[PDB]
Amino acid sequence: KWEMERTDITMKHKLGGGQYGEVYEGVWKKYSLTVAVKTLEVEEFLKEAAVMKEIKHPNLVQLLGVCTREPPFYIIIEFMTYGNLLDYLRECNRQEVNAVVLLYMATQISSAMEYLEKKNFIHRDLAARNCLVGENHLVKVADFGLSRLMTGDTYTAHAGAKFPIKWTAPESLAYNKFSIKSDVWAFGVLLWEIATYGMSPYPGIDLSQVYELLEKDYRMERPEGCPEKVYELMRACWQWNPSDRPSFAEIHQAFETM
Ligand SMILES: CNC(=O)c1cc(Oc2ccc(NC(=O)Nc3cc(C(C)(C)C)nn3-c3ccc4ncccc4c3)c(F)c2)ccn1
């Protein structure tokens, strides 16, 4: 019942200024409803759809349908008007997108991640560039496969593997060890991204030197205007030992009872 017919969608523009891969603005003509359309090798492409069929949460991206074993193949997703969170923060009116709205943003992502934690999913690339902003500041967690779509300024090699270095937990850099706790660390950086209205992490520091810095216990400074308690949440997310890091259940609770 997920199967749609290609011709029921009118295809329009490339999303994200054309830096988010083969994903388009489209319209489900029957409902006059704007949708996002991922277009197409096929076995990875089909496995994405399968995963997304088992994802239902208000702060996670929502499959609407697929067009299958015929090219072009589509994955059709509910449309998020305002696009990615990174660019959103960077270009927003900060009286409208004020500290309350920043908090509401973080609280939404932690709910999404609480849900992924319960489902034993590991995201592996959490960051503001992978979050979507819709009407009334609704935020949804997504995965655009950006490691194949971006450059060495964001994704590059550490010890012979490719990483989004400045979002990557130390044990993942050192052992290719990925877990829900490596996603917590990433969440830490994403909280810093939100609080800075989309500043790049470790400003001015080359991706080359990040691991050694962390290892000597350096972490990023408290952003301007960020409450001490939210900063300590970042610092909790960035414990060297993944065991010492809070669960997403724990983080969500902290926002709830602030
Ligand atoms: C203006 N509006 C817009 O720009 C706009 C654009 C928009 O486009 C898309 C957004 C999200 C996706 N897809 C995903 O998010 N995939 C995903 C989620 C997860 C989770 C659920 C596990 C996080 N795992 N994987 C996921 C799973 C397997 C994968 N295998 C290979 C590659 C990637 C993969 C990703 C997409 F295809 C298109 C939607 C709404 N608005």
Image (tube, rainbow, N blue to C red):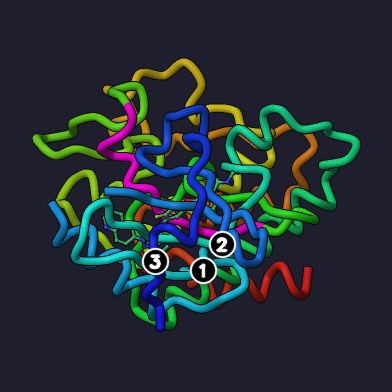
Along the viewing direction, whichever of 1 and 187 lies nearer the viewer: 1
Would you say 89 lies left or right of 27 here? right
Q: Is mark 2 within 8 Å of ligand 1?
A: yes
Asked whether disc 3 touches disc 2, contact meaning CB atoms under 8 Å apart, the reply is no
Real-space Cα distance between discs 3 and 2? 16 Å
Numbered mark located on residue 78 in the image: 2
Q: Nearer the viewer, mark 3 or mark 1?
A: 3
Q: Which residues are magenta?
A: 139-150
Instruction: Give 120 or 211, whichever is nearer the viewer.
Output: 120
Residue ID for mark 3? 5
Q: Dividing the image into four equal quarters, which quarter contains ligand 1?
A: bottom left
> What amino acid is at disc 1?
Gln
Q: Quadrant of the N terminus?
A: bottom left
The mark nearer the N terminus, 3 or 1, is 3
| Numbered tag placed on residue 62 in the rendering | 1
Figure check: 197 above or below 254: above
Residue at 18% x, 59% y is: 44
Residue at the top extreme, as displayed: 204
Q: Quadrant of the C terminus?
A: bottom right
Furthest residue toward front:
7
What kind of element bears circle 1?
loop
Whole-angstrom CA distance, mark 1 to mark 2, is: 6 Å
* CB within 8 Å, label 1 to label 2: yes
